Image (cartoon, rainbow, N blue to C red; front, side, top):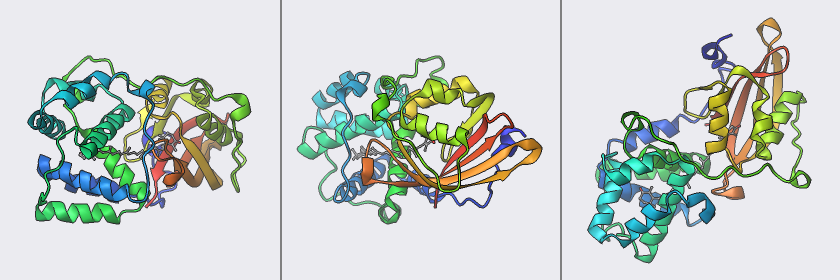
Amino acid sequence: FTIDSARNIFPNTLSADAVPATIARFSQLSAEDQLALVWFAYLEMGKTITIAAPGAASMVFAEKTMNEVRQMTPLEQTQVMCDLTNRADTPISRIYSTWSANIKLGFWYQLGQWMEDGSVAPIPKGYQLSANASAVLEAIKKLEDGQQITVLRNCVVDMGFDTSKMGTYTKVAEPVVPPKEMSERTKVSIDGVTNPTVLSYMDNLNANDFDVLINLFTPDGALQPPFQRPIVGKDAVLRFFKEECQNLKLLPEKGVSEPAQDGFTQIKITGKVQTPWFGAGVGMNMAWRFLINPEGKIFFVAIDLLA
Ligand SMILES: CC1=C(/C=C/C(C)=C/C=C/C(C)=C/C=C/C=C(C)/C=C/C=C(C)/C=C/C2=C(C)C(=O)CCC2(C)C)C(C)(C)CCC1=O
């Protein structure tokens, strides 16, 4: 096996490629239409589900820029949001690109709160979307909740100046929370799968115990998040666990295990995952595809958002 051939296990797994499809339609619109479309989608979503605000401890790297935006005049505030949306080269747009996904989301959550109470320049009353933007908004409102919040997250994440041409820069993330209190941990069960490596992957992720979790991988192993390329090697995979994978709740329900070539094992689990942004408000339907070597170490795992 190679990582590239490991990618193809269980090829009838149908992922939700409506998500990148919708994002690409979104990318065709004007900056102002993009901001207004998301505002209208956000407001509609808030009728039924509520974002859990992040702790102030996780926003320490964004706090000063956020207060700067609030104190700006309305026209400056609108220009900052447009700059981010167009991925313009401005100081705020560069700083934004050094932030982890959760810091970026908290930044836009705070702006959205301030747009509601009138502190930040709101979407003009009687704003009219272009016909193409109107079609995108309706499409987004039609997606199931798990796919809706993934479109919204991926829009937020892709804003800011292109990371490729700020060169050497420190990527910044939320504090690394200590592993969960032992008495506070739960024990997953999976109908049809008792493989100890897969159970330990689930339990350690649910406990935020990334030092233990990373030891489940081969040194050259890889993890592939939904709609992304594989992250290769223990060092990069551990950075991703710390930067992006804290406070998830994984609820695998059932799975199947099959031999693969050379005493490898290929395992597919389906279930739900909750993000801390929404808790039980949004249960995302996920698949996990593991390729495990004869010693029981993860050579490859893909995580798919299901159609
Ligand atoms: C932007 C904007 C707005 C503001 C908007 C906002 C504030 C939008 C906020 C949108 C939010 C808060 C979106 C969050 C989604 C969290 C997601 C998809 C998680 C996936 C985690 C997963 C699948 C589990 C993943 C995984 C498991 C299972 C593993 O096994 C391994 C790990 C891994 C992570 C791969 C305004 C409203 C101001 C209007 C203007 C405007 O543009």
